[PDB]
Length: 145
Image (cartoon, rainbow, N blue to C red; front, side, top):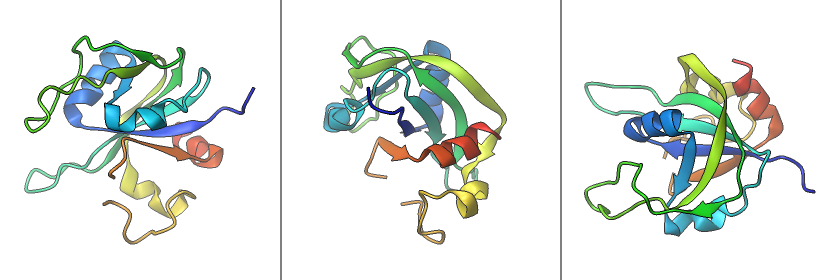
């Protein structure tokens, strides 16, 4: 079989809490093409987006998980949708096994200089993707924190 892959999964504060509790990662129809590339044994790195504004919160790496199921479809509600796409259920999912929850959480901005997948060290922040593959060496840098 193919080698294990490492996936950065982009989520928000509310859904991180759901992922942490239910140990399930899910994406919307628009991104099923990416999650379908996931397989048992792969690792998911949960990225919690920055909170901009006066109540600033840095972008966080909240934890790492092991994928323990093939991608399945389930529309039972578990995640928090947005007001503009209120009927979103993030039906494409995978079961997870907790590997490590970072305490304190990893401030992603502090890792920028050493992350190989981030080639633009100055402008990286600005997405349009729910999942991003990353190299084993970046996974190691993270999970070893």
